[PDB]
Length: 125
Image (cartoon, rainbow, N blue to C red; front, top):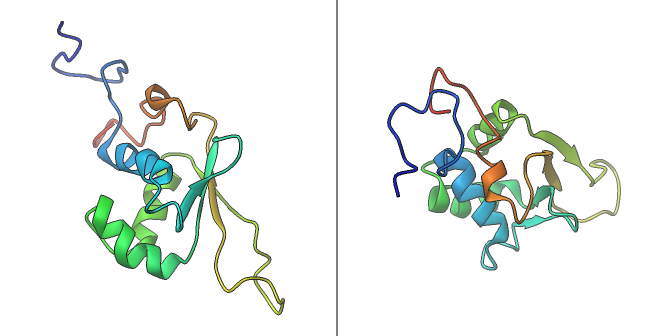
């Protein structure tokens, strides 16, 4: 049953999700890495904790880099918005960043909407 056909221009159907979002969605869902990246109650977004530690172990584990700015940059091309729920300043609030990336085509039980989340056709779609 050939759903995978050659030359997918701007198509979506047989897992046209880029490798980044494929790792990412499962990363948020993963119980080991849940400590440093966990989904919001709705499942439409995800939070990232300890930017330095996450970038140190989690990023070279799922992705092929340790730099966090690279991870965030991909998401800006995917249309995700950064929302920080920790008011970072002279407060007694926890010693971590709350880094929530939100997207309407990113749901916790919708892998087929990750290939509706596109970066560009001039590279991997």
